[PDB]
Each structure stands twice: as C-alpha cells, then as structure tokens.
Image (tube, rainbow, N blue to C red; front, side, top):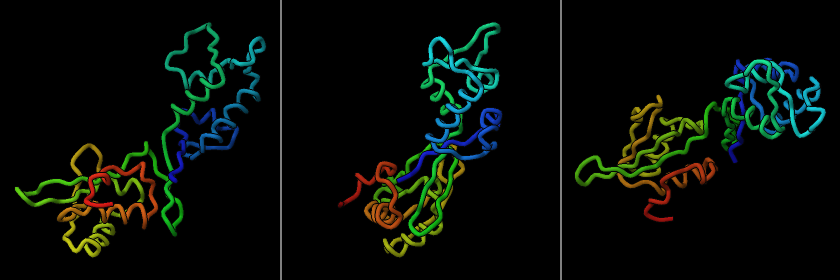
Length: 201
C-alpha cells in the first residue's frame, strides 16, 4: 500500500506551468500522463501525418532530451514521451501509517532491511535499516522493541552513504520486527528484507 509519486524538478517547471503545478509539486503517474497529453494537444504538437507521434517543442526538448540537434524536428511516440517525462521527474512516494496522515518522501522506494549479525563470537544482534524511509522514528521503534523483545536496544548511525540511523536489538528478534512492521504499521511485505531469516513465522 505505498503510493508511487513524481516530484516536479526545476528543469520541468515550464512543462507543468499551464497545469498549475509548481516546482516541488507531487503528482501521481496518471496525473502526469493527463498533463503531458493535454500539453501536446493544447500546443498543437501532434504530428498531422502520423497521429501516433508528437513533435517536441523547445520546452519539451529542453526538459526531456539530452541533445537537441538544430534544424531537426524531434518526434516521439506518445508512450515514449510519457516514459521520458516520468523518468525525468524526481521519484517520490507516499506512506500511510495506521492512524496518521500520509507522509510524502522524495527518492526511490528502498526496503527496510532487517539483518542478523554477530557482535562477538557468540552474541547475535538484529539490525534494522531504513525505518525513516517509511516515516518511522528509530528512537520510538527502539523503545517499543526494547519492551516487546525484553532485550537492549540502541540507535546508531547506519554505515554507508545515506545519513540514516539504524536500530540494533540484542539477540535474534526478526520475528518481532515482522509483528511491528507488518501487523502494527501495516507496511507492505514486498518492501521489507530479512523477515525470511526469522526463527519462526
């Protein structure tokens, strides 16, 4: 139940101007499609000889083409035009947690990762990355899990490129994350990695 969205970047503002959507507006794919189709129709861009094709105007050339060769009409089929527009838009998505207003996020959807690891020769820990991508506060999750698991939790920087926090829980707690994420927060299973390593269903 996460909803994909598209965010209008500065480079595409002239395309979206007539539809009334500014830099930073969030749109569903179906809305982008309507807007782009209307732009082509309103600006008389449909190829008269082949109505499967759209002749790109300078605005479209500028914001979806890498190179605009001079004295050459650039034509794209409708579906290619729409695909390129969607690709050039910024990826985004919307998460709705139970009992709360929806939360918009910029970026590609990344999974929550739940991993078992060794902290010592025989001390297993559970490490949970990308909670914030789903609007979850690692400190809150850590507190909930410390009670649910009856095991110490900590919050630390997650190693890697992204400036994000991870939750660590002492012991093997993957099954408790299944409860928390799938049952309590109703998050989609397809966006969680590591639950298959739990002790039990």
